[PDB]
Image (cartoon, rainbow, N blue to C red):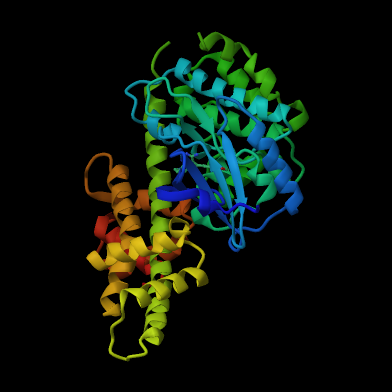
Length: 450
Ligand SMILES: COc1ccc(-c2nn(CC3CCNCC3)c3ncnc(N)c23)cc1C
């Protein structure tokens, strides 16, 4: 009767981290349908609404259908979790595709924004507000050239409370409407976020920027911005006009999603030089955000693995009723499973069969040795991604990040200026204003108490 998620679906692999929880690629055990499952930890994420309100929103979301909005198929609830089962998209984030292009024009910017507005307009007709629209919530349907955009996370912000941790709110500040900051907001907040996104498409720079999260919000709240950057001289007047209307401070004076679809700009440019400088700035901006994000996730994984190594060792020690330092495969599974009850982070192993497979992957690579391998398996996933993000950021292949650049990266990561300079002095007392990768990594290690 009360159907169980894992009776119907098996996890195949991880798709990554989104807002409110992790996303797993899953497969229906009978029909073979692939789906993306977002798993929200009730312990980690507080609800803003009562159960019956969430159920009703979900029943509505399942019935809604639009080409630029993620399809939701199913919803489950158990003791500790919510499972949102939707269509899986394989084209990745819009901005990562954009930075892979040789050229990008207003026609490309217009076709992108028409799609977002068209998705937004439909959802507003149905009384659903996103609130947290940003490039990271804009997925490409597949790898194809003319790939449709699919907006993810519509409706969730109404029912769940956002994380206050910086690793979860990288990038959020540039896109939030000022009225959301003060508490009285409605669907016009999504037109604002779209206007900031459009501003970034045409210039590659946020209209409201600053050295850290609070600086950005101060700029957003004041609400002022300019088209005084030289890359605007190359942009149509009617595009700015649209941007001005979408970024109008008083929401009741701000243009609707529906009316923005009928704006000259959308109408003219969805039927013409390449914005070279914009692509360059977007590429720098994406590189900066991803490195900052990878840095904070690396530090977290290191603190998590420090916690869980000590925890698993004490569990395995107590289970060592022999005292001989060794355990069976059966007991190793009971202790690994027990580590998974206490903690609530492994979305990837939310089933008894999943834990047996991870254990078998570790055994193929004396509980002490098993503990090292089981936990290095967790951290090296985030460690390899750090290095990859460092290499991506270092676009000139110099091998080094300058002091100016660290300041930008640590500003975006909300690591205090005095704090990271002190850490650098401790890694290299003679440093000459630049760090290679291993020094950078050494700094992050010191910034999470290691
Ligand atoms: C609210 O329900 C949601 C939200 C996002 C996703 C989702 N999340 N993600 C993770 C991506 C990982 C990279 N950052 C952007 C999001 C997905 N990847 C492919 N297809 C998807 N459907 C997703 C899935 C569901 C069921």
